[PDB]
Image (spheres, rainbow, N blue to C red):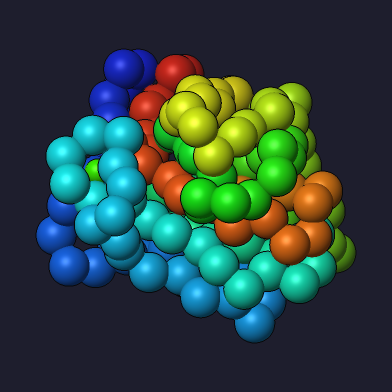
Length: 156
Ligand SMILES: [Ca+2]
């Protein structure tokens, strides 16, 4: 339906809602006015106990077969957290219904002192469901996300 260069999703978190982002694990995912990269608000994740926990977003309705997309956003650790590495991952059901974990970007070191840009391209060849999440190998890190975007690079 879309063409190269089109915005598929854009999240500033400047209204009341998490704009579809939801908890993965027994975590708390909500909007905060304490910190932001742009505007007044960002998306905050706390209460992580395992490394696979984080804020998550279904992409099932956003990304379709063989489309190349570009996923980006700005991240920062919650005040007090030690330096930790953050990346985006897509959990995908393949053609057979089997679970696959696809890498979007290399993990970047992030601190509680500055916002860091994360970005990578993504596509898939077979599958029925797609779930994006933001994770750290540090199982207890808490962190913020702002100015999240997905852009179509190449139509299918
Ligand atoms: Ca914002």
